[PDB]
View 1: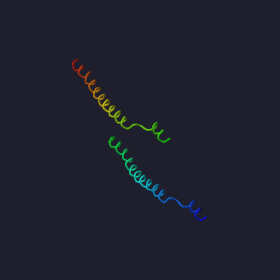
View 2: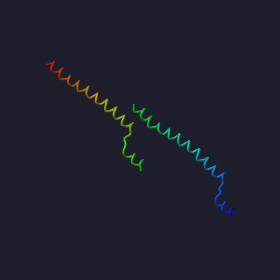
View 3: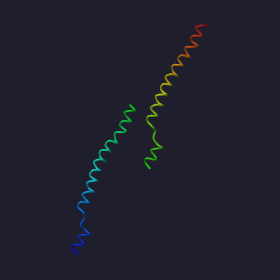
View 4: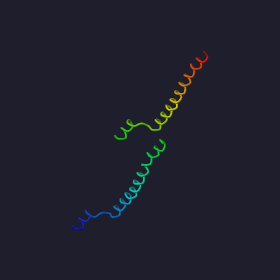
Length: 49
Length: 48
């Protein structure tokens, strides 16, 4: 019964690590592109001048 | 929804800059021609 409950409550450390890897790589990208996206209005203002 | 509304609310800055410049040139030109016109009857009355 312990083994069965463990099958129900124990997961693939590998699968979780994979999901976190993908999420981590995505997050930095999101931050950087947000930073870049702020620039577009700035350049349209430069055009305004 | 926000993008859809934006597509109808705001005003394209490049186009507006172009139109503003155009209107400025036209206004200066008009002032100049009014001055020239005024000069015209001045010359004709001098001819008189």
